Amino acid sequence: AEQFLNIRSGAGTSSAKATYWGGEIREQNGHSLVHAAVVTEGAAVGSAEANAFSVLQHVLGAGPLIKRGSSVTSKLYQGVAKATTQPFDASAFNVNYSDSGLFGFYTISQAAHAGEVIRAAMNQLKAAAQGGVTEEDVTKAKNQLKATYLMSVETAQGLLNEIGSEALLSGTHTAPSVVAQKIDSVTSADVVNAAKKFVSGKKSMAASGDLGSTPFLDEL
Amino acid sequence: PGAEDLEITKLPNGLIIASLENFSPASRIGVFIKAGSRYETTANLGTAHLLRLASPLTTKGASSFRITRGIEAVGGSLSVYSTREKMTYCVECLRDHVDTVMEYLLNVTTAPEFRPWEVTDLQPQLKVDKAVAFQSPQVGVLENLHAAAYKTALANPLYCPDYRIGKITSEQLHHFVQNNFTSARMALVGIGVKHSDLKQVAEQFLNIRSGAGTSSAKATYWGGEIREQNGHSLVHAAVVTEGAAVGSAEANAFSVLQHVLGAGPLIKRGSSVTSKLYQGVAKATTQPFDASAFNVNYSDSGLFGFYTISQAAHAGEVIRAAMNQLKAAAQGGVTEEDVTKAKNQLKATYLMSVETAQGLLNEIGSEALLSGTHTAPSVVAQKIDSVTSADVVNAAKKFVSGKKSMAASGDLGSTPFLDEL
Amino acid sequence: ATYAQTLQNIPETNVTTLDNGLRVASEESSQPTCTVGVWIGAGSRYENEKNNGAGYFVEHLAFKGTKKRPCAAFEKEVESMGAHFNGYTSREQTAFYIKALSKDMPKVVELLADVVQNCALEESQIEKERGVILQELKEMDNDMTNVTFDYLHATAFQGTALARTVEGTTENIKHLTRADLASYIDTHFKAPRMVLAAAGGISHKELVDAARQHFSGVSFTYKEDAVPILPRCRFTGSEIRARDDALPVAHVALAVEGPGWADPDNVVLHVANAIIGRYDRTFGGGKHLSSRLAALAVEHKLCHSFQTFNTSYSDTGLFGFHFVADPLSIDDMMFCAQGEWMRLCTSTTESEVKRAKNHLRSAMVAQLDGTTPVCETIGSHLLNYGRRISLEEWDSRISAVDARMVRDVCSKYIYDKCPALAAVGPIEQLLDYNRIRSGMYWI
Amino acid sequence: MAPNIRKSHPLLKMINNSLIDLPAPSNISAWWNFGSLLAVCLMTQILTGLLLAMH
Amino acid sequence: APNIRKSHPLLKMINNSLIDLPAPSNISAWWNFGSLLAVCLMTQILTGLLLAMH
Amino acid sequence: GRLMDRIRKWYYNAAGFNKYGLMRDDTLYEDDDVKEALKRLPEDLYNERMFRIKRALDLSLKHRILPKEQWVKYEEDKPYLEPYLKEVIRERLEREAWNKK
Amino acid sequence: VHNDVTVPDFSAYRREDVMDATTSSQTSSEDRKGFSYLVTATACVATAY
Ligand code: HEM
Ligand code: HEM
């Protein structure tokens, strides 16, 4: 690093902080399956407000854990099933960037059942914003979260990314012990809070396919 | 022999017939239809476009070959123009040949065969036809505007979407014709001909049923915002709000407000002083540009606002300066003298627009199709000056208040978002 | 009410000349709206090497205001009456005309007169337009079709005045003086060479009274009443190949010296160009199009488009064709094109001329589709043909034409002639003047 | 399809491909004339030769 | 390049007419004479030269 | 009358192209008209004709024929191209007469 | 810009009868062509012989 590296020093050119828009892009293309993703500004990297979302994430359900499973521990999934007839997939979307973030849900479903799957995913998110969270839900998600994380670092890349990601953002290194605390410190409230920050905040939406039966942001 | 009169029979089934012998050495017939891209569904998107280019394919009575050879044999022509909700087939030739060209015009609009091969062979033309049209940014943004301004029908593109080039079936073409080219949605207009003749043909050769077949799912307003970053130095932009429908007297206000704000120079390389908008933007930017009053009036809705073209960097100023220029008019910034000038420009424009054979034939049949009637240039003139100073500033407000839509393209670097105007 | 008749019904075009030389002409229609303008017999051909580009620089100022009514004063007065003012400047014909309510017929003439006579030529504006023209050149330079025809003239009429562009040189634009624009106007915009034409709902008499009023030029010496005769431009079988393998398509234009307005053959030439016609990738016709070249073009993907042309001039002219193609089909296209030309001289069929004549008449009629176009025909006819030529006459002349005539006339102007060529773009495939010169005979 | 029969015909396509449309440097000098003379010599020899071989 | 069987100005020919030449899968014995005829020509020419020598 | 009608059935069996599994139309020589027709054929019909042909070629190289049980029966022969071909030729004749006109 | 392009002067090579830029080159055409084709025609005669 020393006796070999080089190049300039200092943050060189900095990035013009991300301004939130709350747009709506629709891509009509015929493709039978309709992909859609509705989000709101979420939490940025580091911010404790994220931990909540990470938990709210796993609470709502972040992609099956059992091969060809059903995902009962998944509020969202379960919610949408009880709404549509045909095959589909819906999950809790969540990204945490430096000066901002995005949170919401991403769905894939037949074109015709696009309306129901998408809306059923909204109510499913409001019901959680309206106390629809059990202290038991919050404890399970805290495990899934602890599990996921812990597993993600088994592969050489996983571990190297985990290390360096931090070592780059704050030249430090939280021990898997501390990270574990920050998780369970999330309260039942925090969760329903995030849940609300979603239903309230301005949303953005992206879709693609035969958007024939797909709703516009101002219909959710 | 001087000037006759504009007749207009209205046959049973609903097929309208309006003619007008102007003794011009050349006639120009045309089947105006209530067809268009708005009647399309996600399912047959673009079929309307491909139908437009099918005009030269074989018909139950004339082969692809004979259609083109036949018309050319007499120095005739065949064209098809179409808006989001209006299709106009129409031939044109020296008087002495109207019969000849008629068969083809007829066969084309009522006897299509849409042979599978002839069709699939044609669809690649969509590829091409689109590429040329799209050479003018003018068109690209307008497609997107409509996409943002609406949620349906009028939100459909005028040019077949790419993914569907080549997936439009013969069935889709037929069903489209059967469900829209109905005697009650059609009008057989003509010029340089006698009503007795034009009528004869209409009843002795037309067969299709009447009734709007499939009706269009009324245009819902969205108020979208589509931005197309593409590098191209010049930034095209268009900001609008819902406007006035057809007929609507309210529409007459906008036409006046239009000419008041300025609707494109009248003097070669002019300055357009009589143009509030133009003038306003100039006093705002340094480099070359162009800004005008945009205005469309569709059946169950309309769009109104301004379209600008400017350097990328001065996009922010040109666009905003165009907003304030529109608010200042919404806040009594209209003189009774401004309103009177616009009323002339309007009377002028209109009056001139009908000098060309096509202009007149479009003016006639457009009405003869919407309300089987015919306002005299006298009455139309009234409806104009009946616009008051208020009406204008009213429209002006309806804009600043209503929800807007916006379409842009180019190096949008210094271009503002709808929620910044 | 057969075509024939509708022709002999169109009102006659009236013409009356003033003591200054100005010629006023018009065709009266019931039209509530109209068009009136002054068609001057001046252009870049009248310019010499030192002022090439004057008539164009001047074109840019005939609208920025006169002595009496400055910029806003002019525009305001004109914009406010719902009138459209605009014009143009060719190689040997310049024009300025307005589109106004037949009502304003007389105020417009006043305005027209005030432009051709009292152009302000505000030395402040001049420096601005200087930068504008310079800018329009940058643009027009990206119009292959233009570049190609200019070049066509540049070599076909090399060494003469007709080989200059209308817009002029980058140097002349950068240096022309108020004085230059001044004299240009004084020397050329002169009564005996101008023509006040009008079309629409207008009284010829009312028109001419208005003419008398503001178009009150005075003439003392004979010199003033005289119309100069330009020096003859020498045509030259030659070629100019401007190659740039970076442009998408390639443009090619080939032509032979044409006779000139006055010559009756022109009719026949047009009937011929009517056979070969023109084409373009969006012509619905397709493989069935009547023009063999077009048909061939379609069957072999020979060109994005092609077009014949018979550009007339006072004493000379250019009879040729132009096509845009892909680098790799330039030869096949050129081959086929000359093919049809040779066919025109050797085997034109009666059926062809029949179609050609009809198509021609139709175009002839479209040339009078509105007050403006009609007006443009008057201004030009008087200016070029001396008098007005009625469709009834044209139609007559056209009917006289037959296969034999087409062949004789075409042979006359085409067969074994040294053509003028201009090629632009990725033109490596098309090649050798000689190979092309031999295409002029037998196919 | 091929328009002219000079570039399409299985045989002419060859005469045209080597003696008509063949691209050649614009500057080759007289020292490039012997190739064909050589060819003409070959032809002339063969011809006069057959004539002699007959006797 | 890749193979010198399809690129070489000469082999490109032997390969183009006697190796990769596409042929109907069903031509019968009545299609063998083309080459026999060819072989005859070669054989004649060859024995002929031999004879012409004496 | 019903003479050549049975004559035809005789010839059809005499020709024998059905022992290969071909329809009358399959054996048509592909001149310009036929090639144009073949182009208009719906895909299924075209793909089928191909297979029939490819199978026949395989039969020929093999010096075999289909089992009597698979031979096409005179009355089950589908003239899948006949009509298209008619039109094609019809279309051409028109152009022709027209161009001499 | 293409307006600044001029075909050069070809007087050093032009045939005396088409040297004057103000005379219809056409009148001398039949001779210019007549002469050259004569040479050719003669060459053919010789070869023919
Ligand atoms: C490569 C081209 C040829 C060359 C270089 C060539 C050269 C010669 C030479 C140098 C001689 C002796 C000439 C002398 O008498 O001084 C000769 C003789 C002869 N050549 Fe050729 N020859 C050619 C082609 C042919 C061919 C193709 C034939 C006929 C099939 C032929 C037939 C004869 C005969 C009959 C003689 C002997 C009688 C005589 O000398 O005139 N030659 N040739
Ligand atoms: C197209 C191929 C050829 C055919 C069809 C052919 C045929 C014949 C025939 C029928 C004879 C008479 C045979 C007999 O004696 O009963 C003959 C003789 C002869 N041929 Fe050929 N020949 C061929 C090629 C050649 C060539 C290329 C040469 C040598 C350059 C040649 C040299 C001779 C000689 C020397 C004789 C005369 C002595 C003899 O009869 O054996 N032939 N040939």
Image (cartoon, coloured by chain):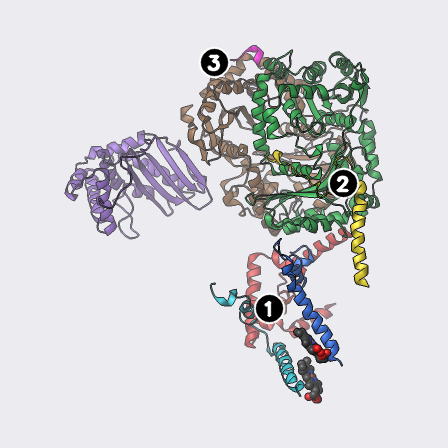
Chain colours: A purple, B brown, C green, D blue, E cyan, F red, G yellow
Residue C25: x %, y % from top left = 78, 21
Q: Please identify the quarter of the rendering in which residue A140 is found.
A: top left
The residue carrying mark 2 is: G18
Residue C315: x %, y % from top left = 78, 33
Foreground: disc 2 or disc 3: 2
Q: Amino acid at mark 3?
A: Gln
* Magenta residue span: B333-338
Secondary structure beneath label 3: loop
Mark-to-mark CA distance, 1 and 3: 84 Å
The residue carrying mark 1 is: F22
Instruction: Reply yes or no: does residue A62 show up in magenta.
Output: no
Q: Nearer the viewer, residue C276 or C232?
A: C232
Quadrant of the image where one finds ligand 2 = bottom right
Instruction: Give the number of the disc on residue B331.
Output: 3
Q: Are marks 1 and 2 on the same chain?
A: no
Report whether residue C346 is seen: no
Mark-to-mark CA distance, 2 and 3: 73 Å
Secondary structure beneath label 2: helix
Secondary structure beneath label 1: loop
